[PDB]
């Protein structure tokens, strides 16, 4: 029961629909996410389906859908510029919606920059209606009115030409749905971007335990989490801030060439098995010193919260914990998805805790910085 | 014993040194080739090594070395333009040489466009001297004078930050060395490109059984194979030609945006195990109708050549055969390494046959076209 602001007169954002990436080699990118991250290739458009300008590979893990897109032709102006500016990265964060027309009319009236006005596509399995507007940077939002669409992903997509015996042979990673999608902004842009979500989409600010305590000194960022009225989609917005060390938000914006998605968090209900199986697929994660766990166990000595998972196993797998007196979450961060120090992924499991892990900024900073100081900062 | 032309006064091309690819996401490209194609990540340069403009991932399988390169910074003019024009593709075909200075002086005198004049790099393990010239398209040749260099690949490269438990868990693919590297040229360019190899590098034309019989009607190409004096490096040069169907060389040049490497052939001494294990890693290859093998077995009835490998297994794995009365080769072609219909790979094993498989143009055309004609060309 919190201040959610005025209830929108019409329109609903049900959930994240899919995330679309603009990449240099969609075939190889799909292979990376299926083999390393537990996805399965679901659907495809390309030369073989009559799509002559764009190749599209759709991969799925439970409710999580990622789409990888590349150009077929030399000197594709739009995709080419994006690739050169940003490297591989997120282009579209798509939302499943009800009452598309109200949402789009309101967004347009309130100043949204339109990429494509309402359109529909159909095949043997039904019809889907869409619209696309710009958000921060070169990122966009497609609203997807799927009317319990019974086809393969979306109209026009076809089965992949081949099955993949490599991805098939690997163990399940148990990632269920997209928990949140974080967008990094350049200096001083967080408030105007958050205001866009409030005005254009009638989102509101989501207040969690992380908003109640300052972590700027360690995190070197400020964040505002924007969410739809029913709080089913969460869009954190970061900007750099003055802290004890150079801001990773500034590094992101420098190497991404502007604002963009920093991380996508994937919610799991069995993080130990998830991380064991992601590690078996060759994924790497932040290295966590043993002192983090020694200090965490000492802090937990005065807490009434009960950690259900085996702490020795969490320590072995370098899974992080954040808690208050009413619950806790588990989280872990992958290494970067590319050479540029830009996008990474997060795996998160919640036990009655609606925050984002901000306590770990201080906890990891203290454990890692102290050890490096002892090592002469060499 | 054939006409090799005049023997060069100084200089030797020993072998292929490595192939460098300019790609959108070198981290993910290295992962594709290690997991799908049997390579292992060997060495690295990037932010962690002091390389602030370029990330470089080096992967190796026996003598075969592939290097994947991406830019770190937005709007890298050279790498960006290459990426937008071509997609992911080969940038540099590097040769290991002796007497670098003669080779470079001669190439420069004879009109080579220089990318970088002779330079040297050194670390704790020794020194290597290099030079780079342009060849066809945006492709270049680096000459590598490695003086039995005892370090990790080349000076300045470091160990990868992580080992990869995915690539480690997969079965060996038995690819030994680069057999040949084929370059597709636009209409009418084959002769001038072949003449460049003869004049600038003192290569000569390699004549094989494939040059003695015409296959243009089926292959829709013309080829000249250029080779160094000792015939240790083979560089086929293709151009489109008029045949029964649209030329795959024309499709390549259209989607690559000009000349470039069409395929890299990797030599194996156990093709059955190689293909079994590449298939277990999720690689796909051209589908071959059973009629190809029925017709091949009937043609072999009048030949004195003895196929050592089990033909039923070759048929199961869709491995191709080409032969004359003095020997045979086995070969197979992967599907494309990217969405654009440009680069693919070949696995080849030779049994006393120095050709390139040109007999399979007709054999596969006849088997595939006949079946499609029966299927109404739908
Ligand atoms: C809305 N919101 N707020 C936080 C989040 C996170 O995912 C999130 C939460 C905690 C951490 C990180 C990300 C992270 O990268 N590190 C490492 C680090 C980076 C700089 C300085 C000190 C430590 C953390 O400790 C989110 O989604
Ligand atoms: C120097 N040199 N000459 C040939 C080569 C090859 O690798 C090579 C040899 C045989 C074939 C292919 C490549 C190939 O793609 N197909 C399929 C096909 C393509 C168009 C029309 C009919 C059939 C073949 O049958 C090379 O390296
Ligand atoms: Co997060
Ligand atoms: Co070949």
Image (cartoon, coloured by chain):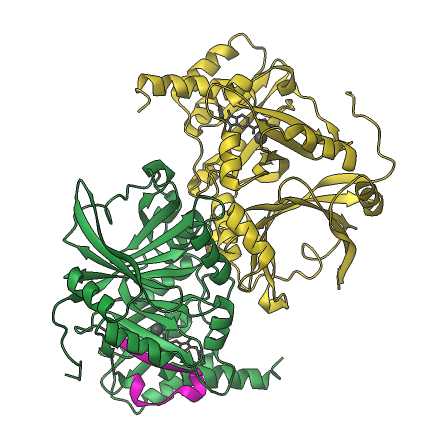
Chain colours: A green, B yellow
Q: Where is residue A288 shown, x and y percent of the image?
A: 45, 76
A213 inside magenta stretch: yes
Q: Nearer the viewer, residue A277 or A322?
A: A322
Tell me which segment is drawn in magenta. A210-227
Picture quadrant of residue A197: bottom left
What residue is at 52 percent from the left and 81 percent from the top?
A246
Query: Please, is residue B282 above or below residue B240 in the view?
Result: below
Residue B80 shown left or right of residue A241 in the figure: right
Q: Residue at x 80, y 39 (%)?
A: B110
A350 vs B165, nearest the viewer = A350
Taking the image as shown, residue A342 lies to the left or right of residue A319, namely right
The picture places residue B353, in percent across and down from the top left corner, at 63, 22
* Residue at image location 79% in from the left, 51% down from the top: B147
Query: In the orientation shown, which residue stands out farthest toward the top?
Result: B302
**Percent position (x, y) of residue A71?**
43, 47
Percent coordinates x, y for residue A72 in the rendering: 44, 44
- Left or right of A278, for residue B149: right
The single residue placed furthest to the right in the displayed view is: B9
Between residue B89 and residue A369, name the one nearer to us: B89
Q: Residue pushed farthest left?
A: A9
């Amino acid at each position: 029961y919190t201040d959610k602001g005025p209830k929108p007169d019409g329109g609903k954002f049900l959930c994240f629909d899919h995330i679309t990436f603009y990449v240099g080699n969609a075939k190889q990118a799909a292979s990376y996410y299926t083999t390393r991250m537990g996805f399965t290739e679901l659907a495809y458009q390309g030369l073989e389906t009559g799509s002559r300008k764009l190749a599209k590979h759709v991969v799925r893990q439970n409710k999580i859908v990622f789409v990888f897109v590349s150009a077929y032709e030399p000197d594709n102006t739009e995709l080419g510029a994006h690739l050169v500016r940003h490297g591989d990265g997120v282009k579209d964060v798509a939302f499943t919606v009800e009452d598309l027309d109200v949402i789009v009319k309101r967004a347009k009236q309130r100043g949204a920059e339109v990429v494509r006005d309402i359109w529909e596509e159909s095949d043997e399995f039904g019809t889907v209606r869409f619209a696309t507007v710009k958000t921060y940077g070169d990122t966009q939002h497609t609203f997807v009115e799927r009317k319990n669409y019974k086809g393969l992903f979306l109209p026009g997509y076809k089965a992949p030409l081949y099955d993949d015996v490599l991805a098939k042979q690997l163990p399940a990673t148990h990632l269920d749905f997209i928990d949140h999608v974080v967008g990094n902004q350049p200096d001083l842009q967080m408030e105007s971007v958050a205001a866009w979500y409030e005005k254009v989409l009638m989102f509101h600010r989501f207040w969690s335990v992380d908003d109640s305590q300052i972590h700027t000194e360690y995190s070197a960022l400020r964040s505002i989490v924007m969410t739809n009225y029913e709080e089913t989609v969460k869009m954190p917005i970061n900007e750099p801030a003055k802290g004890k060390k150079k801001s990773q938000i500034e590094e992101y914006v420098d190497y991404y060439g502007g604002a963009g998605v920093q991380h996508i968090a994937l919610n799991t209900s069995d993080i130990i098995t998830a991380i064991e199986n992601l590690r078996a697929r060759g994924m790497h994660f932040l290295s966590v010193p043993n002192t983090y766990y020694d200090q965490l166990r000492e802090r937990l000595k005065s807490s009434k919260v009960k950690i259900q998972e085996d702490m020795d196993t969490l320590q072995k797998l370098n899974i992080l914990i954040d808690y208050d007196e009413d619950g806790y979450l588990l989280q872990i961060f992958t290494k970067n998805m590319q050479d540029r120090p830009t996008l990474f992924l997060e795996v998160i499991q919640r036990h009655g805790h609606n925050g984002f892990g901000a306590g770990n900024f201080k906890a990891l900073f203290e454990a890692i910085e102290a050890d490096q100081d002892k090592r002469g900062n060499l």
